[PDB]
Length: 128
Length: 189
Length: 135
Image (cartoon, rainbow over all chains, first blue to last red; front, side):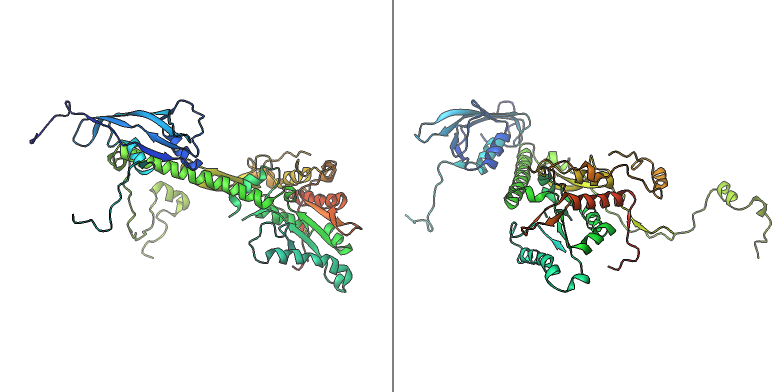
């Protein structure tokens, strides 16, 4: 729909964020994850060390403008890959705020965590 | 003689360890050679002095040992020139230990290295967590919350004054001169 | 006509390392809570510590009234009983002289060390002099 859309009330973003992982090889970096209030744990003593957590992140966001968000909704369970390759929901993401400019959760997992699928490219693309 | 308790304990200090240890054969040389009547030896084992290592000084002291300021240590060594010890060293070579009971902490290298690691680690963690919470905050609440949080500085420009004499209120200058001076001096002369 | 005396009055300091929120390690020489002159310093040295265990109080006006303290400089304090008395049994002080044994090693001797600390205390109170001493 082309034109100008003063549609700040009728707007909403409801995207299913990529399942990032994060490997906890070291103790200075589990301390970084624990500093983040959004990482709610079911067993708050659960030794995360030497594990691969995954994040079923899905982010809703209201907009008040074409850039600044009106409210940020980050929720979704947090699993741990077990050695037997049967995960379990050990935590919840729950990030709530007002005047947001970007999801910090997704921003966090963008740099500190990693995308499951990373497409590799050729040195030279094949002209089919 | 400034002999240390550090005899290949800490290491990584070239021949410092063999230089201070060898200074300690002067005790047997003072009996076995002629020069006893000319020189007397008052070998001082110099303990942990502050003024690198100064950070962990607190840490090591928590073991019930004493480290010294330069002043303290200098007071201790001047102690070794009081007429009482001078007579004493003349009678036979004095061996003073100003180590502050540091000789009793076992594995001093390993215990020092443990203390540096624990203080450095915590210093770098809090540095990293503090900067990573600062860039997260700036992402969430934009650069506009941090440009209005930034303050404009003012840099001083030279204002070269001619420095005329400071003129007091008449009441104050009338006190310093005697009151009888008024209209006494010809001001042409 | 009295000899010039090395007497220090400087406030003894200890080490205080603090890590702020932003992980900056700051070092500082901080007034020792207990030790607040040289006499006290020598008494702390005399007592030693728990790990050094093998097997007197004076009123002043330092950091409150300079003038009275100046007044009590040329008045040389007589000691009731020396700090060498207050060295605990089977306790090696922090400052101590050694003696060579007949066996051919250096062990802690109580008598010499007792004499050394007495010296120290006397310097702390009255002050040592070095008149006509070439160094």
